[PDB]
Amino acid sequence: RECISIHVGQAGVQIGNACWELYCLEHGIQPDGQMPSDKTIGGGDDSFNTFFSETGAGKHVPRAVFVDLEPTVIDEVRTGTYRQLFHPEQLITGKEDAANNYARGHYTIGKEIIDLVLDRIRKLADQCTGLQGFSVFHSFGGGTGSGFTSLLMERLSVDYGKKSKLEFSIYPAPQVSTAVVEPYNSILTTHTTLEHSDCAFMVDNEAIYDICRRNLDIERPTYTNLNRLIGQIVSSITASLRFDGALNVDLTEFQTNLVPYPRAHFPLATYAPVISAEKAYHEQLSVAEITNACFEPANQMVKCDPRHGKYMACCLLYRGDVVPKDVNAAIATIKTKRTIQFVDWCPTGFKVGINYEPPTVVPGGDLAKVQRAVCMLSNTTAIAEAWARLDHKFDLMYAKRAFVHWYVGEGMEEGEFSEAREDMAALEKDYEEVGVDSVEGEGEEEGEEY
Amino acid sequence: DLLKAVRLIKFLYQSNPPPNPEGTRQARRNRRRRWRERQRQIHSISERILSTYLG
Image (cartoon, rainbow over all chains, first blue to last red):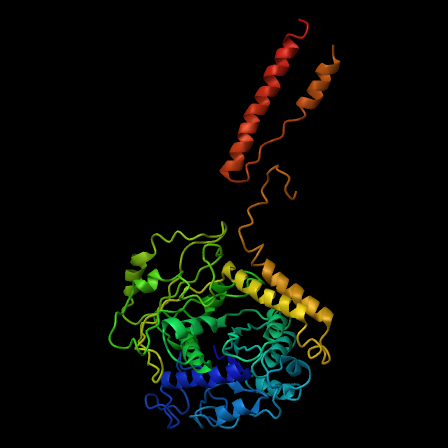
């Protein structure tokens, strides 16, 4: 449960400092240097006070190794709005910036600090015996991007053994970013980060842009509001190991009931019962419409039709704050009808997880006193349209051959791109063809594939 | 005598497959209707014509 937190890239370091200061305001870590609730230095030693333990200097500092060869993100995590609450001396800067080029990181520009990050992970991996995996904050191409996550994952699978490799593989919106080459690294992701991992997640940026421009109506279509909402989703997922109690539905059975298969590796997220700062005027606190607008595309990160995507698993999660008996009271609300199209060889029921202790609210953003949540996270075959969109983008770019000579004279290979295409095709066909109900193998005589 | 008769046994009574219990009710119903027409048209008209063949 003392999992090693890696944060590379500009998005990784950005949401790393943001989310760890959200833990600081969540666990009470005041800018004094220590909490006023529990007087143990740095951090506590409870079941949930376990992210913060003794590694640095006896002060139980927050535990996250921050490495990126882009030096300006290391500067603004060193010179942001908090100067001592992170690791006082363990953040090492990067000397030369990759500057939006992924392929330099895996072969040329990031190879000098691989020994240093191996030393850091050997420092932070011989620690306390609780280690259920890795809280990887993956990125594609912002800073170094997929380079350090890729080399860390491959040498962690061939050198550290078979530990779980929980990923936050962000698939950002091209509108808010500036790169164009991003399909190349997003499809090399399958070759270098997908097979040798063991568990993964998905965070997105298109739906937050869509609600911020149209629905939530916040005039901030940049990475800052994306960080402000992904901080909420990271706090929501870490509340399992952060809010221990009677209903501590933690990571232990979570990693079991997420993924069924090798290449059913990619879950989905549908957290959006959000109430805005311009909606923060004592409005309706709803437990009905947050159940009634689940399969509508508002909560979905990628606009997909639920009418075509069959589900082999479904993990329901309603984290509130009001009553532990409201678990039963919300069981007896809407779950009785639920005629949802399923694979003919999967279960039907919905798991339940609540955290009835109320949290501490993040100030200075676009959120009200949020207390309750809905998230229908599962592995769905309805992301086949999103991966077909990505493959259409990559097929058009490979017909255009943009930055091919940029991405071949450093260590890559056209046959390596062919094998990456085959890996992407395997991840497709485990969701396109095998992922749908394959009942057409029993027997009939019409002229089919015998 | 035996030619059309015995070779018609050797074909037609070698032309009866077991049904398919795997599959949903629609294809099973189609195989059932083809079965209940197949054995009726194998026994009825063939032993009618082997009855009134020449006596």
